Image 1 (cartoon, rainbow, N blue to C red):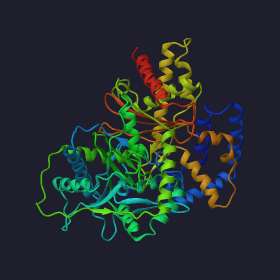
Image 2 (cartoon, helix red, strand yellow):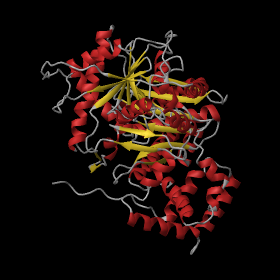
Image 3 (cartoon, rainbow, N blue to C red):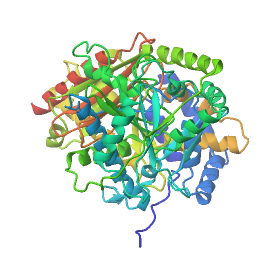
Image 4 (cartoon, one colour):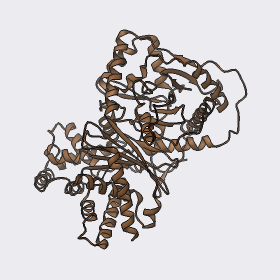
Length: 591
């Protein structure tokens, strides 16, 4: 017995997407660039033209696949993306600081966290995970079944992803890494029952004491390099039988727990921002960066000082499902243990050794150098907006997410003096195997709003009208995007369909306007969670920002990133303007 299958991802009508595209370009391209683009768009959609041919191609594809976009998206967005996954692909999450003060407290928490994941896994293994709903409609739960017991695998041309959860005899162990040393930890007894918290704690003590050495080679840091470099080093690494066995154990593990060293001197108010760095990239070659396996889909991180969080491989899922799993786990850690497994002898967790040769050492050194450059160029800040959360916008009958997005547009305009291509993730989970699509936060309504907000010749009454119009318009774009009515994925599809049809790239995609539209100076995402956490990721362009937030009832946790190589961007500065924009908007509405 089961409810009806989810609707299939739709292909939107050609003219609808093209009209929306032209409207989204208006505030971020010049008048002449727009005029030229309109010409190209009309050429593209002319009767009997290229556009209609590609459109029929996608409609055909939708009739022959479970989701016309799923395979293409996984391939183009992740598997064929060759930049390192660290910072540029794998999002990190920071949890509230834990109160443990000694090793006992640290390991008790790590054990509870582990037990929590195994509890969640009961639903994955039995396919009994409850279906989530949005606006009365069921959502696809496929992403949740890709998180555990999975791992990305480097390839010379493109990467692949392995999921061992439904094999003949699925893995029964996690992997724990401490001071760069990996250990295979069975978390189920011979009869298939769990280890309980007490038993896991006992095993973690053994692992801890078996890895006190701090001068081992950080083999794991190899996973942080450019995908072509890692594919090369990976092939070399697994030539040795022992190395291959160790790599296989790591790849097959349910998940990985990283027992981190405490970061450098605090340096005061920059504590939260530095911990975010620890969760996203590890902090450095001499830190915590080698205490990982970035190909692993799920890595939980627990440091000695109480700083905790996770970093996940992006090919498997989106932010919302990841933090939902996190919420479940954290909630579990707060409940009292009800049943302790019978006391029985426990084996010694197996240390996964690596035989290092000069070649491998050389690859390790190159990986350390590459990552150092990456980390030094990352500018990340975390800001807790304590003034209000979802409560205020709701009291004004405005969508909190749309309110926040318009505040960001205002902050950006106040710094730059112009609007910019902006991306906000939309979840397509109402559809079978749906992932994401784009919400275009920069619009003519948002532009009109930001231009009038600080104009002393405009009445307070008109500023309020323009503000509400921009917020409501954004919410409109949001709701349509979630219903599969946006246009960005559709345009990508038409582009990929042309490749499959052996036709040259249509002019609309080689147009200056499209380049501008796809160059997101602001790439954003709302990732709500019950736990007071925050997610973060690096910008998608050298001169852009990455902005992520978790709106709570009375406050909002924000994450903002930028690259130091671009002198025009600064995360802390944008954060400051964002804080004032939010406050100014509340002040205007409340008057």
